[PDB]
Amino acid sequence: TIPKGASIEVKVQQLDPVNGNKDVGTVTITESNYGLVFTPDLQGLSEGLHGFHIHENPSCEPKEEEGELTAGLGAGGHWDPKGAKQHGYPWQDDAHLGDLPALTVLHDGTATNPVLAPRLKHLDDVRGHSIMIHTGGDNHSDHPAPLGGGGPRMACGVIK
Amino acid sequence: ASIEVKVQQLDPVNGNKDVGTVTITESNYGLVFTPDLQGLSEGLHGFHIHENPSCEPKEEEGELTAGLGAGGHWDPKGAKQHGYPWQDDAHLGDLPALTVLHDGTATNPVLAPRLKHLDDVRGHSIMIHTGGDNHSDHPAPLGGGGPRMACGVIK
Ligand SMILES: [Cu+2]
Ligand SMILES: [Cu+]
Ligand SMILES: [Cu+]
Ligand SMILES: [Zn+2]
Ligand SMILES: [Zn+2]
């Protein structure tokens, strides 16, 4: 059911530039007294922890990258309006504002565990951007791998 | 400043086994619980702070229930209701669920936004349940975490 209070229901697509994207559920965004809450209702995804971030552009389209059609590159990089210029924790002030807690996909491929982004206070702020779910996880650092080790873009949705 | 909590998988019979630690630190948005666990069953697990600084099993109805010595959910404000970590009228001990990967390890940190001071959690215990946590007493009271799987005392 639509949650109580203002909310944004984002459609999420498993990305595959060649075989076509596949709708795998939604991520509903609400406003708690401690920041925005992202509640997933996804299915058919790879088990494990997955990097979860807000990206700059309101697009999930693929883009040619060095001769390879790469999924979700149209979304741009991690949303960093405050110019932290480094990937970090959801509770770290000098980290990309788009850095959310990692998403958990169970063994059965489903994801329903909500996560909080304490630095995001208003719904309107995330409108006009995209939400990304990566193949890899997120250690909330640019070391030993850039952007938390998220790597490829596995699923994506545009926040209207 | 930090608190390193030693965690053990509970088993009142053969004994408990050290499964790692959970380190508690302060952030500008609340206490962060960073696990470094291993040897646990994969999946999402209920994660809460319980009232007593004990992980001892307690005999109940002819049975020796594990981790019962820790008491119920830490609830200093008397919310008398289980809920979300960002829910003000829920137990203050209600933390975000913990993720154990397929390989049995847990290293993903979680934030408890309503907990602002490190000292406030001292003298209690942290519990990891067999089941998950739907952050409500409905349909199952206390989130449906079921049995107490692992536990550590917060010093
Ligand atoms: Cu698995
Ligand atoms: Cu991302
Ligand atoms: Cu518990
Ligand atoms: Zn980032
Ligand atoms: Zn509770």
Image (cartoon, coloured by chain):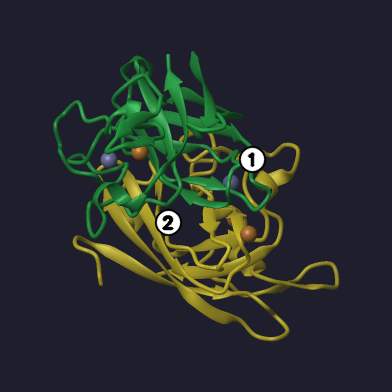
Chain colours: A yellow, B green
Where disc 2 sits, the SS reads: loop
Q: In the image, what residue occupies the spot 51% across and 72% down?
A: A43
Chain letter of disc 1?
B
Return the x and y of residue B24 as percentages of the image width and height: 47, 24
Which residue, given by chain and number where applicable, does mark 1 sit on?
B39
Residue A106's place in the image compared with B64, above or below, is: below
* Crowdedness near tag 1: few (<14), some (14–19) or many (≥20) residues, C-alpha within 10 Å: some
Residue furthest right in the image = A67
Please give the label number shown on residue B155.
none
Where disc 1 sits, the SS reads: loop
Q: In the image, what residue occupies the spot 49% across and 47% down?
A: A101
Residue A55 visible at all:
no
> Left or right: where does residue B10 sit relative to residue B54?
right
Three-letter code, disc 2 = Asn
Which residue, given by chain and number where applicable, does mark 2 sit on?
A113
Residue B95's place in the image compared with A61, above or below, is: above
Same-chain status of marks 1 and 2: no
Residue A37's place in the image compared with A63, above or below, is: above
